[PDB]
Image: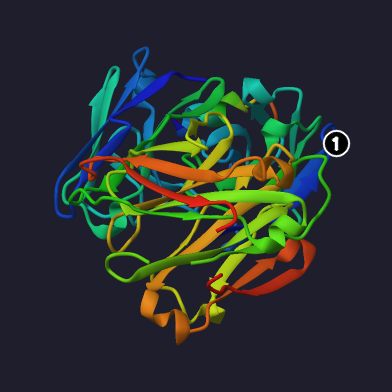
Amino acid sequence: QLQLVQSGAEVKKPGASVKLSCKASGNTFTSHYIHWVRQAPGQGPEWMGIINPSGSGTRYAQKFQGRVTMTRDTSTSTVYMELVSLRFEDTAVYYCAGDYYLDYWGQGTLVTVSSASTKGPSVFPLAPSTSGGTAALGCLVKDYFPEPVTVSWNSGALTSGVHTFPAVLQSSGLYSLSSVVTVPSSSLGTQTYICNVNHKPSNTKVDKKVEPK
Amino acid sequence: EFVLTQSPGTLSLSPGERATLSCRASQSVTSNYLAWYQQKPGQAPRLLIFGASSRATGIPDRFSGSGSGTDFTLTISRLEPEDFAVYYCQQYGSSPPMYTFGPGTKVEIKRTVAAPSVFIFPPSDEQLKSGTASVVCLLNNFYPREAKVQWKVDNALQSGNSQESVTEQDSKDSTYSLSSTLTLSKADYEKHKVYACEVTHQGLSSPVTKSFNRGE
Amino acid sequence: FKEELDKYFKNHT
């Protein structure tokens, strides 16, 4: 019943600081070592440091010494990690983990370090012959910030043949991705195809009907 | 931070087969403090093995670890569908406390070679009205993951101006899909007529080219 | 390992 619940996603400007929290749930009757581990996009996990069960002692990875501080509040079963002088390279999912061997893990907190402002996506059609009668169509989800966005098709009715690609960070500092689906070319006159785009950081919900041009 | 290598970078195997993953340290691992973690997309890592050979609570018996000195192994006796994932070794130490994850080995599903279906998409009229033009080349349901995409504009080979994205291996047909996007201003896009992407893949006896003419 | 890790933090209680 050892479980950890982390705080919500953060967006910070370069040079600012961020303070993340990690609260134990379930069996909160003893105290455990707590670690912080981060994972940048496309990279493997990187250990940042550890705080002992009482909170009287810490040890940080050399790469983060002088930049990271861990504290804990025994009264609330909560551990905190503060990272200062944020850099572009600090954009990552930050995890807490418990016990000697990182036996159990929180769900992760996304931290984005960027000068960009919250911006909802512009959704454009990827309009649809093929030897097997298979047409490809999709939606281009362009120029949003920050991550993440969600895409569904026909309000979740269409899932077969759907590919929603991982986002790429453009040189503008904004993210872009495409979602595509393959359909029978014969259905292009019978079925309607709508991509449902949800960008929760900007409270933007866009439905886009994709048609042959 | 310890120094670790994992071989191979990618292991391609079928369900039911035995998987052997290797981790090598630059120097002898003090006290055999070597652990193994599993990670799937969108999830935290999961502890499998600690102390070189001790299985963590709740981990199936098909996972086992062995090693000493510089050379350590994780064996999955028979791969189940849920076992295809990335696996990280990790060296740890007590004085001072230090935990260092290795670079990782991806265990993917091997399947028959599948050629990509290729599609090219012109920019929408809506996007063009905004002063921007994105051209998208889609490579759908191919295996293996390796491929080459070459952009040609009025038959001039392009370089350095595209961005690519690849899906995770599909759970049902074990294929990959890839997008390549060329982004141009409306004025730059209107300078040229023929836009093409050419795909090279093991499943293709000859490169496949899809193209369109701006205007038609 | 566990006893060694505890020992590292012994001077801080």
Q: Residue at x 73, y 43 (%)?
A: B187
Residue at image mark 1: A16
Secondary-structure class at tag 1:
loop
Q: Quick check: A5 left or right of A11?
A: left
Is residue A84 positioned above or below A153 on the image?
Answer: above
Q: Residue at x 68, y 25 (%)?
A: A64
**In the image as oriented, which residue stretches furthest toward the bottom?**
A190
Total marks shown come to 1
Q: Quadrant of the C terminus of chain A?
A: bottom right
* Mark 1: few/some/many CA within 10 Å (<14, 14-19, 20+): few
Is residue B159 positioned above or below A158 on the image?
Answer: above
**In the image as oriented, which residue stretches furthest toward the top?**
B27
The amino acid on which the numbered mark 1 sits, given as a three-letter code, is Ala
Q: Residue at x 35, y 48 (%)?
A: B85
Q: Nearer the viewer, residue B154 or B161?
A: B154
Q: Position of residue A209 (x, y in %)?
A: 61, 76
Q: Position of residue A120 (x, y in %)?
A: 76, 60
Q: Position of residue A40 (x, y in %)?
A: 59, 38
Is residue A140 positioned above or below B20 on the image?
Answer: below
